[PDB]
Length: 427
Image (tube, rainbow, N blue to C red; front, top):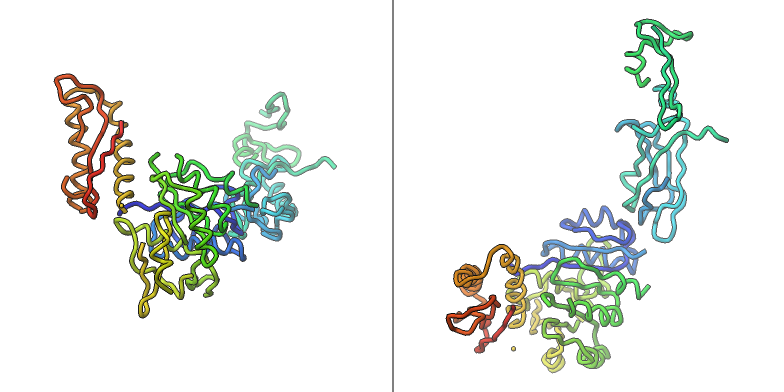
């Protein structure tokens, strides 16, 4: 594939407010993250201009109302329904904060109290009475919860109580017809029958799976700190970026001061793609694009998806990695990327191998377990070889002897393009 679930943290002009969500369409990121004005732009865009050749994208917005939404606005209309039926539609959020968190709304009750009166649910309300937002406001996430209409500036008496509360008091009759003094059919059955800032990104970054984390905005300082998460947390890899003139000097300093865990493979690069939701070209910040280039290959480097410049030759391009850095050059129209790949193979393998650990719990360890596990991993490894990726391709924790111990997976694998077998041991 070779797996490819991205992760974006940045500003966004619509909800969800401070939450992850998976994105698989443009229209679902557009839908929720309403827009992106020019700091959030690059995050809407962030979704948009890779998702053309990318799989799944995780995004994060930086900015009785049970749950203040986010990215809502002020005259976003509210609709009060009576059992999935519109009664009032002139409600409207009336106060949000900076994040669109719904602070205040105003629902006119003319219609509803009417309907409510009309159906015995006055001012009780509540149960079938619901309130939803516009479909939709810019922003999402909200939860308005409707209570009652504030009024505080063969017959039987039925007194319903809930909680000692005489919730209801009625007199009904068991006799059809019977009415109260109002000819209100108080026949029971009927009666009832009738309704009777900078820090925030670093603070933010969280558990979620994924092989690519790019916020690109940052430009240095977020990334710089973020990289030291992308590093940390063994079967994951942290990619970083900047760009470009003074930057390349800087970058060559920055990446060497320092972000090599070799599990962390960092990078060295601001796009000029035409994102067709803003049709415009600024420094959209390249990393995102490269992420979509990442989602493909064994490890990626080839043409870029739709450049109209990438922030030129030769020396600087050749120099930059050993440090993670990647830069993109144009040869007679069309781009390629130049930049012991080997790591990814290994990292991936190692990560995958470890996960298989779940299996261990499943069974006991024996010679056979050597097999089985071995076979399983082997199958995986072999597959890698067959597909290509590993060439010239196991574990015995105990020394080769009768004696054995728990199994650790040690493997000597060789990335296809490298005449070297690396020994990795996972235990």
